[PDB]
Image (spheres, coloured by chain):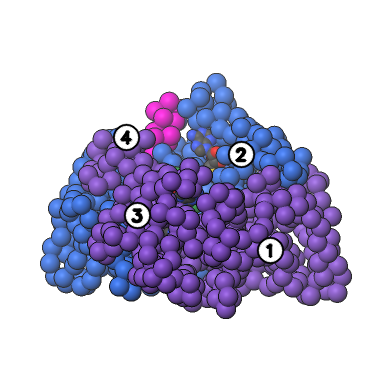
Chain colours: A blue, B purple, C green
Amino acid sequence: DAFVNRIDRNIPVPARLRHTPVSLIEAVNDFHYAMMNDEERNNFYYEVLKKHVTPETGVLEIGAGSGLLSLMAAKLGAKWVVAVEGSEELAKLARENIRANNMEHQVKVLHMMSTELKSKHLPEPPDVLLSEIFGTMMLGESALDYVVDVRNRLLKPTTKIIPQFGTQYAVPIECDALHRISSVSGWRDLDLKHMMTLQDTVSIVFAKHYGIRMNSVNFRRLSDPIELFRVDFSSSNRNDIPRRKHFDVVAKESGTAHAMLFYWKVTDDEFVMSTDPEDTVNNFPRDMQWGQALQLLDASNGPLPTPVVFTEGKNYNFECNFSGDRVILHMQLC
Amino acid sequence: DAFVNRIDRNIPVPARLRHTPVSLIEAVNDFHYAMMNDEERNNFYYEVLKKHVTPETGVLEIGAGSGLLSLMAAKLGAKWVVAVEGSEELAKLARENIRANNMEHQVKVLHMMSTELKSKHLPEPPDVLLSEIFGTMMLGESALDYVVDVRNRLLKPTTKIIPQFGTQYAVPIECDALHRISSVSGWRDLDLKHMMTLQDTVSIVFAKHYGIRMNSVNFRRLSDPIELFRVDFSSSNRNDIPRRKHFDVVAKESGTAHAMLFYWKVTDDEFVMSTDPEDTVNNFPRDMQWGQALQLLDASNGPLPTPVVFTEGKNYNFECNFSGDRVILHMQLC
Amino acid sequence: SGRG
Ligand SMILES: Nc1ncnc2c1ncn2[C@@H]1O[C@H](CSCC[C@H](N)C(=O)O)[C@@H](O)[C@H]1O
Ligand SMILES: Nc1ncnc2c1ncn2[C@@H]1O[C@H](CSCC[C@H](N)C(=O)O)[C@@H](O)[C@H]1O
């Protein structure tokens, strides 16, 4: 779906853009730059890889993008590095970056999805599997499913999977700024409350999509964090996460729970990659590429949504329902 | 196309949302709430209407939405108000709000596009035509087009059109925050420059889509504002705006023009509705519903984008190309 | 708007 065919004819389009897929341009310009400029994400990968990469170790990377993580493994002295990348253009660009860094003899980039990758494409099973395909929801880009496919077919029992652990969290919040742009009551004496019939209390929406950064606005956490699930990328699979779980939450503050905020932490040994707003205060790129997810809360199913109200010390039961692929979930007060 | 049809079976959807089209839910949840809580925008319409509405005046509104502006006209004592709303479900909701405010005798809502509105649908030609269908780009939702059509067919020579004037502005800006998420150099000694090939220096992108509020980040304006065009809604036509215009811009500061920032001003009598960041520092909801638009600036058409660099006192020539309907435009340094 |  060429970019130039999606643009009015009176508007100039430079040659470098004309024939590239519009969806690729959109994705790259929304988060790839932010992602590449997340210095702490880059440092996380470098430090974990530094512990495992020796001149004898082969490295397989799922989802090369710019080739940065592949370049890191080679920089660290890896025997060989194979990176796979589903986008034809990104694969070209990753090879250009590789040559620009003089690592052409060390890193091969294959244009294909990791599901199409077969043992004949690698010299031997890799000593290290490397990926960064986490979404705003941790499993939002099907990270576990892709790692699982590769794990079943191409690895060996001694392969190191980076990163090793991930945990997804939820916490109910009061947030006046969010409330202000997701609800209405009226203007002066004019009642407009029937617009509330359409309030979307089902979807998971990324904070970026609201045009809001959580670190930048005032919000109150109304309970301790709720651990929705935990994954070990070397042994878990998506069906280990139950389709429906229940959580009993004790209110530590009084207030209105406007939304559930979702964030996650990924770890390997002592190193941590977190999207908790409290950890990203001075990481603007991370907030722009991952940020956090939100779900507006409705207390019942009346013709109008009902505010979820917390009183400190009371218990509140939430039912968590997952989609079939575990990419989407929903939290409902019971 | 119903909401429930796009959602995983395991996720509960309240009855109020089930059948409503996913496009309606998305638009309402993204912009409508912020819009209705734009208190200055509401005040603007009330104060302008207050100058023209008498017990004798008939009022037609294009784009009823929640019904707010039609309710205002009724509150000021209009003889009759007809509003047209193209969304079927929104039309129903407006009627609900109209009933909740006991104004069923004064306001009627018709479900249809204004282009299908005919004189037989009105008591008589209105003394006042009212609309708020401005986008982030002033003409981004075809405001001039819809008003002109109604102006050709349904009004009378003494009909007051609200609002009367609009002016679209552009100003080159340096913004490090924007630069950090729209460009890449590399990480440490790893060069990633070739990802720059896909930098989207063509599209008009809303600040909100970048996850940024212009008010909340440091940016420098590098010249005086550039007036792209002005409109009088009672006499202007689409073709008043040339398909192409040239602007000679004088650098008032030295710096890198990372982007062109676009904002507008709509006026009627002494009253003003502006999207200039300076004017919306204390209006979060406006910044979320309208905000500003941005276009990243490329100097030439080589394999990689070239920075536009301003030297103070020097002048720079831009070619502005508009789309056929004037909804889209593009600023290119010559 | 970020990732997923
Ligand atoms: N299963 C898969 N197989 C091959 N490529 C994949 C994939 N899943 C996602 N991708 C691609 O991998 C990239 C993930 S984002 C790029 C991350 C990369 N490690 C970096 O730091 O630059 C995207 O460009 C996407 O197109
Ligand atoms: N030409 C047209 N004819 C009928 N409805 C239109 C229209 N153009 C836009 N709309 C509708 O008008 C609404 C504009 S949003 C403005 C809502 C309302 N005037 C208020 O001030 O709150 C949208 O709901 C959209 O569905």
Q: CA distance from mark 4 to mark 1?
A: 44 Å
| Residue B5 - label | 4
Q: Is mark 1 within 8 Å of ligand 2?
A: no
| Residue A282 - label | none
Label 4: few (<14), some or many (≥20) within 10 Å?
A: few
- Nearest-to-viewer mark from 4 and 1: 1
Q: Is residue B93 left or right of residue B292?
A: left
The amino acid sitting under disc 2 is Val
The amino acid sitting under disc 4 is Asn
Q: Earlier in the sequence, mark 1 or mark 3?
A: 3
Residue placed under numbered mark 2 in the picture: A22
Residue placed under numbered mark 3 in the picture: B108
Q: Earlier in the sequence, mark 4 or mark 1?
A: 4
State which chain disc 2 sits on.
A
Label 3: few (<14), some or many (≥20) within 10 Å?
A: many
Q: CA distance from mark 3 to mark 4?
A: 32 Å
State which chain disc 1 sits on.
B
Q: Quadrant of residue A210?
A: bottom left
Q: Residue at x 32, y 42 (%)?
A: B20
State which chain disc 3 sits on.
B
Predominant SS of the magenta segment: helix
Expressed as whole percent of the image width and height from the top left, the position of residue B231 reads 66, 62
- Nearest-to-viewer mark from 2 and 3: 3
Expressed as whole percent of the image width and height from the top left, the position of residue A239 reads 28, 35
Q: Who is closer to the viewer here, B247 or A280?
A: B247
Q: Which residues are magenta?
A: A144-154
Q: Is residue B248 magenta?
A: no
The amino acid sitting under disc 3 is Lys
Quadrant where the C terminus of chain B is found in the figure: bottom right
